[PDB]
Amino acid sequence: ARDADTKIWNGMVGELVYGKADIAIAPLTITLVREEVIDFSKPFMSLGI
Amino acid sequence: ARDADTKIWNGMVGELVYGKADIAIAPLTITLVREEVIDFSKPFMSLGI
Amino acid sequence: NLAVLKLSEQGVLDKLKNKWWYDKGECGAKDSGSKEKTSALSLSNVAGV
Ligand SMILES: NS(=O)(=O)c1cc2c(cc1Cl)N[C@H]([C@H]1C[C@H]3C=C[C@@H]1C3)NS2(=O)=O
Ligand SMILES: NS(=O)(=O)c1cc2c(cc1Cl)N[C@H]([C@H]1C[C@H]3C=C[C@@H]1C3)NS2(=O)=O
Image (cartoon, rainbow over all chains, first blue to last red; front, side, top):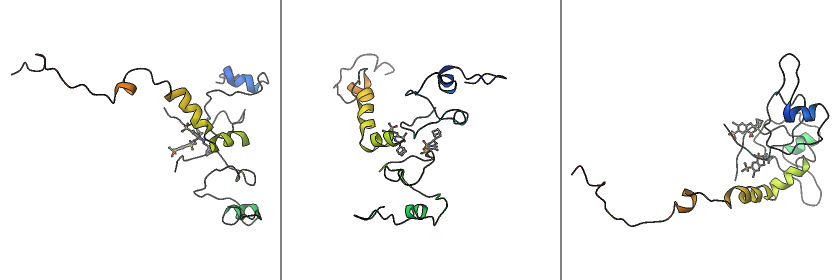
């Protein structure tokens, strides 16, 4: 997730935001706050809380 | 769908390909061959046959 | 974007999901939920009588 007041995305987000990692095939959830910094394909498996 | 042997999209997808429409809020199923001519958003409702 | 739709079209996602969730039915109720035992009456059943 992002940091408060500095927007530092850690974790698997910042690996793609900050140019570290090239692609991420992983259980990652399409949100609203993630489309602004990275892009997602069409979803391949559905779920819920 | 496309016509046999001519690749002429009738129906609503042809209305987006041939410049006659602008957007299609509709019960429209994301297939493969519809991706190569017109863009889709993320899915909003899931179903099956 | 064009690749994940091929796997959705050809059921490869279904095959992988079956392999990694349903072929490894291990614990209890999934396997033994459709079997039958006859009876043997013990005293814990009939006590209030
Ligand atoms: N039954 S499931 O959760 O494993 C599952 C879920 C999905 C699959 C395929 C499977 Cl097998 N592909 C769909 C895609 C197909 C087309 C329609 C939406 C997307 C495009 N997304 S999905 O709805 O996320
Ligand atoms: N239960 S359903 O089919 O009506 C349905 C199906 C979908 C919904 C919302 C609903 Cl209510 N939104 C999802 C999107 C929302 C976010 C999370 C995945 C995608 C992004 N697409 S979806 O999986 O197509």
